[PDB]
Amino acid sequence: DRVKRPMNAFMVWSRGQRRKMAQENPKMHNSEISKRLGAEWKLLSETEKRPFIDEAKRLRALHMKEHPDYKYRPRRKTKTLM
Amino acid sequence: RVQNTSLEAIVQNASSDNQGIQLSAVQAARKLLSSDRNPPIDDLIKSGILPILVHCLERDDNPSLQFEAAWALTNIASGTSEQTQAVVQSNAVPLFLRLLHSPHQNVCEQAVWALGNIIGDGPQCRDYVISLGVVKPLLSFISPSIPITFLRNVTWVMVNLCRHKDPPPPMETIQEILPALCVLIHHTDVNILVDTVWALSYLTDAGNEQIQMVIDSGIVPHLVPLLSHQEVKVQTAALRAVGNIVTGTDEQTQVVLNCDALSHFPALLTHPKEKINKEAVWFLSNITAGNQQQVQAVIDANLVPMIIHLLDKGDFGTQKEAAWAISNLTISGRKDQVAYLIQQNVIPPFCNLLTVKDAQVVQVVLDGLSNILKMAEDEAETIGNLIEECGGLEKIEQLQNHENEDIYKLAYEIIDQFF
């Protein structure tokens, strides 16, 4: 279970849960913490996932705006001018 | 220009049975829509000209009337989503697709352009135009005998076919486009090359399944060399594209590394452009966040001194990415790999970022130092001295009163266990 940036909704959610789970169960290995976090993510409702979905979208939007040649990107729509 | 001519007369003349009167009216509508970058799209939509322009597309007997009407509709579709949708609801797309087989070049090109603006509106329009069969005739235009200006437009339409992620374009469509991007990635024209790579960067940003489609096309060995391309606009586009791939699985990240991607990074890390340095470190941070073999690959590439070198006396943006790259290595690296990091004088510049105002950076750096101490159990005292020598222990103690819960809680915990 890798954490690459920009993070998706699950990764940002796991980031907070990872630290808590480590403290509450110091005798649990990092592999088992990732396995349980991945499974417990499946139980969350859409309302509980929405803050982390919006954060992932926010991180994604910034990652695209911080493109070195963002100004010279191809645009979605163009006009045929005279 | 709008305030000084009857739009109603244009609309009514465009419905006239006289071809000369009709052409002049559609031409006037085109000029109204293409004389500046702020045309009166709403006024011409409200005037009822859309059904007339759409009907003109069917007049194979008047290629000039088809061209002018496609031109007018192209710029109407170039506006907001509401104005693009108005063109779609006029059922113009099936006629544009028919015009892709027109024997008149300007009619084809203008139909291509109009379809590009519609596809670029969003995933719904994109999939609508895809489902009607745009990809096959569009890619058939890609040949050695196509005018360069047309091919630039074709590649731009292909970019829009790859753009949106919710949902991404269909698998079958991605699999059709990638062989064409393989051809276009060898083109000498900078505009086509940049657009081809941007299309790849959108595909590689669409998810690990789409990243795998890109890999399975065989094009990654042709994208990686572009990291050292002479045109900087090609380099940055390629750097983001491959950067998106290494956000995938370890297997997908390894494909990039097997293409000797790291060989291009000495030049990228010393590039004059600071943003290119920041981007190149963000890439490497996603590598050091991988497995131990991939951390070793960054080591064998002689990049660790350059990452540490950029961590120190670097612009703030690049230093943040360098801190991520270092801390990620402490999470994934073996004892010897973090030992090598220590041997290269990583502690002074790493600890110098404990005073930054960004709360996330301090959190990332403290986690790294914590992992460093925990990894060298026998020599934890030696590292604690190294942290103290450079003033790091002083900065950790100042962070014991930091505002963030995770920061001051960890600062106390680090000091309890090793100080």
Image (spheres, rainbow, N blue to C red):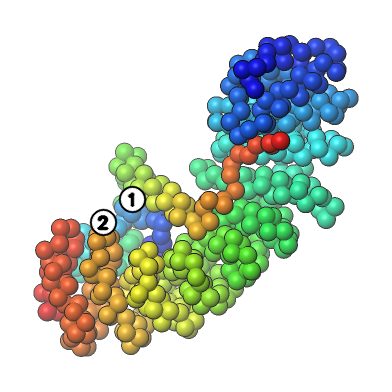
Measured as percent of width and height from the top left, residue A10 is found at: 36, 52
Please give the label number shown on residue B253: none
Quarter holding the C terminus of chain A?
Answer: top right
Measured as percent of width and height from the top left, residue B343 is found at: 33, 88
Mark 2 nearby-residue class (10 Å; few <14, some 14–19, many ≥20): some
Q: Is residue A41 above or below residue B214?
A: above
- What amino acid is at disc 2? Gln
Residue at which label 1 appears: A41
Quarter holding the N terminus of chain A?
Answer: bottom left
Q: How much space separates mark 2 and mark 1, taking CA atoms? A: 10 Å
Q: In terms of secondary structure, where does tag 2 sit?
A: helix
Instruction: Write down the quadrant of residue B220 in the picture.
Output: bottom right
* Depth order, front residue of B370/A70: A70
Residue at which label 2 appears: A17
Q: Residue at x 17, y 72 (%)?
A: B395
Instruction: Write down the quadrant of residue B118 in the picture.
Output: top right
Mark toward the start of the polypeptide (2 vs 1): 2
Task: Describe residue B236's horizontal placement relative to residue A24 as left or right.
Answer: right
Q: For the residues tagged 2 and 1, is the chain the same?
A: yes
Q: In terms of secondary structure, where does tag 1 sit?
A: helix
* Depth order, front residue of A29/B419: B419
Task: Describe residue B77's horizontal placement relative to residue B108 as left or right.
Answer: left
- What amino acid is at disc 1? Trp
Measured as percent of width and height from the top left, residue B292 is found at: 41, 77
For residue B399, say whether it is visible: yes
Task: Describe residue B344's horizontal placement relative to residue B239 as left or right.
Answer: left
